[PDB]
Length: 50
Length: 51
Length: 53
Length: 50
Image 1 (cartoon, rainbow over the protein chains, first blue to last red):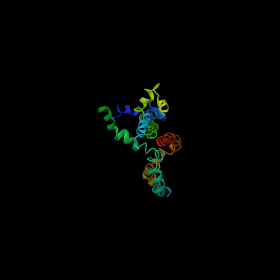
Image 2 (image 1 turned 90 degrees about the horizontal axis):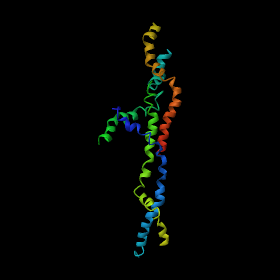
Image 3 (image 1 turned 90 degrees about the vertical axis):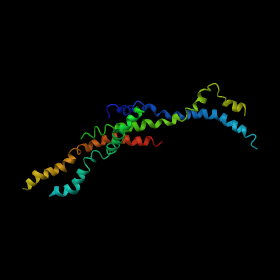
Image 4 (image 1 turned 60 degrees about the horizontal axis):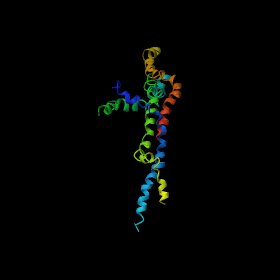
């Protein structure tokens, strides 16, 4: 059973440099402002809600 | 005299908690969980390859 | 005797296999929205928010 | 006969009891580097805490 199924078991090492996930805020840094433009339109749409 | 009492309670701890503990007391998780993924989920590893 | 070697050759794998996949979802939670952070390099008209403020 | 109690069978009890540690008593010091193989799994629990 470990003749070939160890492949997924030994593939866990090549992904060690994956610790860089903290950069997830980097799009959130920007795209949230980019969707803030979308968020502004509903706040533009708040012009008429009163 | 010393062994018979030792064999029962202390060397018992030095036997029953020696071969699965003395070296492996932190390797029980390297004994059972090792068998959980690479022996129990061993057939489940083929699942990603099969599907 | 050999569990300190082979039952423990995965002592240096469960440390790794558990750890490596941890830093995966956080990046993947921003790729569908990352288009606006990348398709809008000159189109960061988030400025136009304040040009339209 | 006490030695026969010892050699014939109690040494076997030592093989049952003493020898159950003879394969781990010298490795009890190896537990300290084996800890570094095992505490490295313990910090793997700490890595996914955040």
